[PDB]
Amino acid sequence: VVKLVKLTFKSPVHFGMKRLSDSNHTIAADTLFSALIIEALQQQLELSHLLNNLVITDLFPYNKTSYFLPKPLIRIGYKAFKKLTYIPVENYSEYLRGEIDSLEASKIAESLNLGKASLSTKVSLQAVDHNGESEPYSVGNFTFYPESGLYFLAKGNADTIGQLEILMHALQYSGIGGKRSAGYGQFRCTIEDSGKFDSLLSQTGNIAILLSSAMASDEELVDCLEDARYLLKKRTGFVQSKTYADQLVKKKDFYAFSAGSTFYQKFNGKIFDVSDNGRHSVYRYAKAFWLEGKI
RNA sequence: UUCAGCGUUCUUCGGAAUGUCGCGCAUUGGCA
Image (cartoon, rainbow, N blue to C red; front, side, top):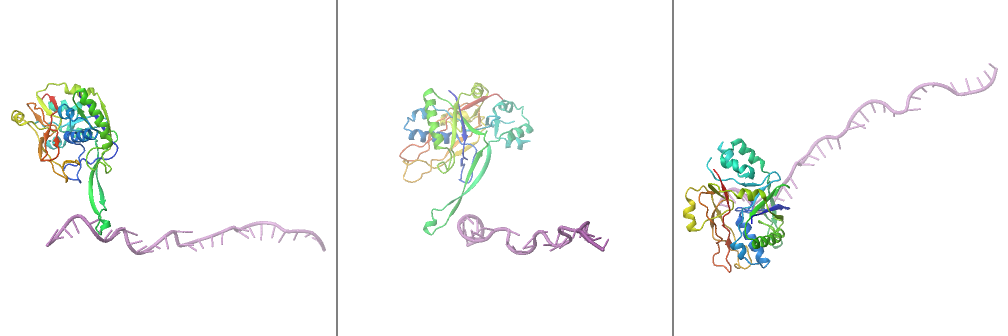
């Protein structure tokens, strides 16, 4: 049951990539899954549905004009083609067939208006009272245009879909990304049946494109890599919880194929464990959502 | 010789702001 989940952001979001100063306009499926797990644990729900039947996608840019999917890594002005990152759903088939030209790719890049990124310079006055000093730091945020929003597609049974609806409503108050609970990431989310995507997903093409940041199991990896065009993205971070350890602990470093990576042989994903001797297992979504296309 | 005032100017010409600062310091950065 693939359900579109559109997110409208009221306040700017941080979405850090490596540092607090930087910012991204989207987040990986794992970052969303980790937020969904944290929420389910707060609301005292069973994690079996999320860990066994929920399939999600990286949040993708959406505009009133169009919904943007990630640019497939398919061999085809090379600058114009490399600058392009997201292609509207209507132009995805044209891009796959090679019917797109460099000027058309430039127009597609200009078409997206997800938002306007910025850097907010904050200060910490915690040490001023102890003969210390104010400490400047920078938070990179991204402000969506009013029509613009981030959407994700969630697939699963009816039970996990309803659980997702509950977690999503709680999540909007919780927020997403970094510096949430410090002014950022408040969003309001709608869950609906989308005719566009379900029709798009009902295609049996010769190539498979990874909607979500995903990694195959070892046995899956050996068949999948042959003839694959892909971009290994390091997935790293600290553990966010009150019960994992007394102090803040980094997760084990993970590498996942990025969204838009094209694999000839489809691989199902796996919820990996990036924990290192903690009081609970830190789950890292790496399951795979596939858009089959014809090239 | 008496009887009366009547007309014309109602303000004018200059000067209309000027000079001086136009953010500084601390954290940060930089050097070590």
